[PDB]
Amino acid sequence: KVFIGRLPIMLRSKNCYLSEATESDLYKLKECP
Amino acid sequence: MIVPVRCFSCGKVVGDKWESYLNLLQEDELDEGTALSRLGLKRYCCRRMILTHVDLIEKFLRYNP
Amino acid sequence: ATLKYICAECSSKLSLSRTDAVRCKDCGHRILLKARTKRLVQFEAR
Amino acid sequence: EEGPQVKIREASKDNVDFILSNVDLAMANSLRRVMIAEIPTLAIDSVEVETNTTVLADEFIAHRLGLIPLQSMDIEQLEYSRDCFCEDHCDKCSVVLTLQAFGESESTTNVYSKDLVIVSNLMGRNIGHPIIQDKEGNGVLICKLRKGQELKLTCVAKKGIAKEHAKWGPAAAIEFEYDPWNKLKHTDYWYEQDSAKEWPQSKNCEYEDPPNEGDPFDYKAQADTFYMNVESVGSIPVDQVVVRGIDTLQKKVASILLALTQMDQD
Image (cartoon, rainbow over all chains, first blue to last red; front, side, top):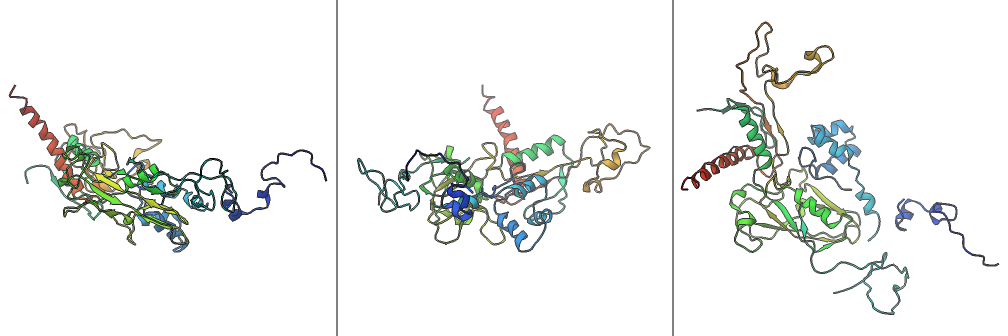
């Protein structure tokens, strides 16, 4: 409901898109697998 | 990251023998050490050259533009 | 036939100048590289 | 004939196992080195990169293009840049190769040395030809590329030798041995119990008669016989890599006599 700042997320953690993504998925993201 | 044309130490051409060797693995199903002798690589110097190089390029290739 | 910048993904010769922001036609991905220079570059063969 | 003779053993298109007899060691080696570093050859020494999108960076490919062996049999009639009166190169001292590639194939396109193109006048002479020995016929894999990756070059090959760089040398290796049964005792074998067993034997023992205990130590014995084996890359037929050897070396030993002359007038 209300905004209260931003929490810098850690890579490959639950909130990182990468946790879910796969091999082929990544390269199209540019992040090295 | 692409095959090393020519052997460091020794000097002999070796840039072509990639696919040839790589094939003696998947298709003709063989064991390294022998594969090499067949490709003509006899002495360890110009031997280690192939047996080691890791073809990163293929990984590189897989990006985009 | 001449150019300037590029889509870091949909690589499509873009080009622009002052105050034209820094986006792309559709995909916004405000990255943009700059492509080579026509003038040939020369190299040492060793 | 007159002196130092030979008795070629095995011999193919790439090797020339042979036996040099009745020469001085100095001479054997002297030759050896000559073969390795000073035989004039041809190769790329200037890449004018017009366009490249590959993952290999410009100067990378560059280096590679140099290594890629090129034809050089008539070399002896293509002046070294530094001597040809043309401002920076001409058909009379250089060979030009072009290179173009495009990612048409929806699956990795290979750029091989066969894709090179000669665009300078050859003047009708075996030279500047990307040497191939690959079964299929596409030798030396220069580099790969994907989707719409391009690569427009332009090379210039020149003379040059393994002193100015190895990319020129034709040698690539050279066997050398002698006194397979240490008779001059040019060594002192290292052991744990018995040299003989622990220190392997050479295929080259046969061609020379074994020891014979009792016998005292032969001291007046020098060094006849050497079991070389000039291998080769291809830029030159294994023979020339051995002839031109004995040749170049010889020319040098002359330019000393020649200099000893231009120096007698004063």
